[PDB]
């Protein structure tokens, strides 16, 4: 009599392991005629409470109504599955991070980069129309995926669930200074996400990983407490400089909403 | 294991202490922090939290612990949180109580640091 049974773990065809780390394992596989990625989550002290929470939080991620949002196709409830598990469609180009920084075959041009920015801004504007907000999605280049036609899509499978440790931040270079220091309840989420978007703009402009020479702990402590900021690159157009600066305003309240920068990025298109 | 390294080799205790001093400074110096005394400088839990993030590759949001603890209880909470990060990283539950670190029990302090050293010797 549950509203959802989730995806049957027994119907997953696991083909090849892609990664393993602190958060779990990623596999390429197949399910009901789909090429998929499976994330098997690693959770210490799994409990019925956490399992209930996982099963309430996953349905919110099944967003099929926007081209720049990649849904979770479904999730395997644990029990009966061996571990809590997420499934999404396989995105052939991988993450935006992969395409920008690990791309061995080609370098995406700046017209494509501007389209990526527009894609991401449209997806985030849509996400911020949802009520309530999807808890705990950190926007960065690893949590945006590039689909078969080069469309950028916000990855809903990369949200942080309630039982995943809030005390460990693995991509602080994209996080707003106030979000390094204050609880999410005390921060305006869309303004914090706009800072992340500004860092994505910086990444698209420089084709460098922000603060690549520093550990995550160095980044978080220096951005939060010592005013460390990305250096605005030389020789970029005044319009791109101006957009980056307004999106990275030190005052969260002065940062634009995503729906206000979508038309700006639309006019920047050249394709 | 840590009974002999502590008790019946007083000059060898100093060897381990100098080794641990070197290891924690390898990492904490990256935040412009220096440790000269293991007897007190980990008692308030702050450097343990910062050390775990340096060793395991994450930032710890400042709302998750007390960066400037103002009570014994906040220091205990910092040490307890650092112990949780320790278990998150694969180490088994630390033997000392949180209070043992806050009270500058050198054996409790040295055991926790040595276990971090045994695991993370080669992290750069
Ligand atoms: C084309 O490759 C991917 C497509 C992907 N498509 C969709 N989602 C992915 N990741 C993901 C991330 C979190 C999740 F919960 C789930 Cl279910 C999936 C994907 C991860 C992908 O690659 C993951 C590992 C990529 N690295 C890149 C180089 O180093 C080793 C492999």
Image (cartoon, coloured by chain):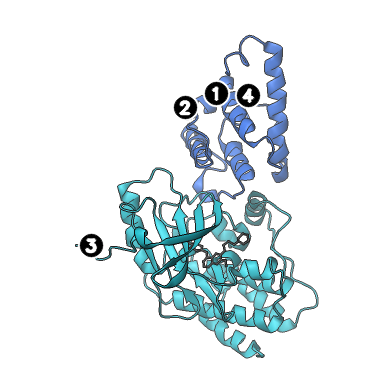
Chain colours: A cyan, B blue
Q: Are marks 3 and 1 on the same chain?
A: no
Figure quarter occupied by ligand 1: bottom right
Residue A77: percent from left, percent from top = 33, 57
Which of the two marks, 3 or 1, is nearer to us in this view? 3
Q: Secondary structure at mark 4?
A: loop
Which residue is label 3 attached to? A2
Q: Chain of mark 4?
A: B
Quarter of the figure with residue B51: top right
- Upstream in sequence: badge 4 or badge 1: 4
Res. A159 in view: no
Q: Secondary structure at mark 2?
A: loop
Q: Are marks 4 and 3 on the same chain?
A: no
- Dot 1 beta carbon under 8 Å from ligand 1: no
Residue A1: percent from left, percent from top = 19, 62
Which residue is label 4 attached to? B39
Q: Secondary structure at mark 1?
A: helix
Q: Is residue A112 above or below residue A233?
A: below
Q: Chain of mark 3?
A: A
Q: Are marks 4 and 1 on the same chain?
A: yes
Count of numbered badges drawn on the protein = 4
Which of the two marks, 4 or 2, is nearer to us in this view? 2
| Marker disc for residue B108 | 1
> Alpha carbon of mark 4 to alpha carbon of mark 3: how far?
56 Å
Is B94 placed left or right of A96 in the picture? left
| Marker disc for residue B100 | none
């Amino acid at each position: 009599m549950n509203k959802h049974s989730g995806i049957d773990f027994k119907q997953l065809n696991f083909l090849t392991k892609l990664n393993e780390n602190h958060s779990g394992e990623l596999w390429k596989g197949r399910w009901q005629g789909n090429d998929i990625v499976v994330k098997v989550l690693k959770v210490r002290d799994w409990s019925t409470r956490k399992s209930r929470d996982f099963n309430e939080e996953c349905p919110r991620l099944r967003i099929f109504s926007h081209p720049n949002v990649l849904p979770v196709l479904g999730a395997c409830q644990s029990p009966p599955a061996p571990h809590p598990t997420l499934i999404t469609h396989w995105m052939p180009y991988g993450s935006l991070y992969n395409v920008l920084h690990e791309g061995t075959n080609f370098v995406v041009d700046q017209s494509q980069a501007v389209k990526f920015a527009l894609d991401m801004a449209r997806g985030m504007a849509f996400l911020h129309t949802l009520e309530p907000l999807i808890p705990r999605h950190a926007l960065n280049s690893r949590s945006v995926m590039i689909d078969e036609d080069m469309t950028a899509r916000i990855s809903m499978a990369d949200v942080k669930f309630s039982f995943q440790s809030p005390g460990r931040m693995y991509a602080p270079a994209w996080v707003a200074p106030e979000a390094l220091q204050k609880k999410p309840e005390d921060t305006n989420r869309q303004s914090a996400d706009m800072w992340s978007f500004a860092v994505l703009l910086w990444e698209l402009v420089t084709r460098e990983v922000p603060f690549a020479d520093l550990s995550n702990m160095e980044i978080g402590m220096k951005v939060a407490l010592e005013g460390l900021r990305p250096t605005i690159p030389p020789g970029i157009s005044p319009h791109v400089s101006k957009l980056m600066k307004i999106c990275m305003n030190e005052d969260p309240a002065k940062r634009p909403k995503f729906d206000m920068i979508v038309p700006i990025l639309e006019k920047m298109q050249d394709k | 294991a840590f009974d002999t390294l502590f008790d019946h080799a007083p000059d060898k205790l100093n060897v381990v202490k100098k080794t641990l001093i070197t290891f924690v400074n390898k990492h904490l110096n990256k935040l412009n922090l220096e440790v000269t005394e293991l007897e007190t400088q980990f008692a308030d839990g702050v450097y343990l939290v910062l050390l775990m993030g340096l060793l395991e590759g994450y930032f710890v949001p400042l709302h998750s612990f007390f960066l400037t603890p103002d009570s014994f209880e906040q220091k205990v909470l910092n040490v307890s949180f650092a112990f949780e990060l320790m278990q998150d990283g694969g180490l088994e539950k630390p033997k000392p109580r949180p209070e043992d670190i806050v009270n500058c029990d050198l054996k409790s302090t040295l055991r926790v640091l040595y276990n971090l050293f045994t695991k993370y010797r080669n992290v750069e």
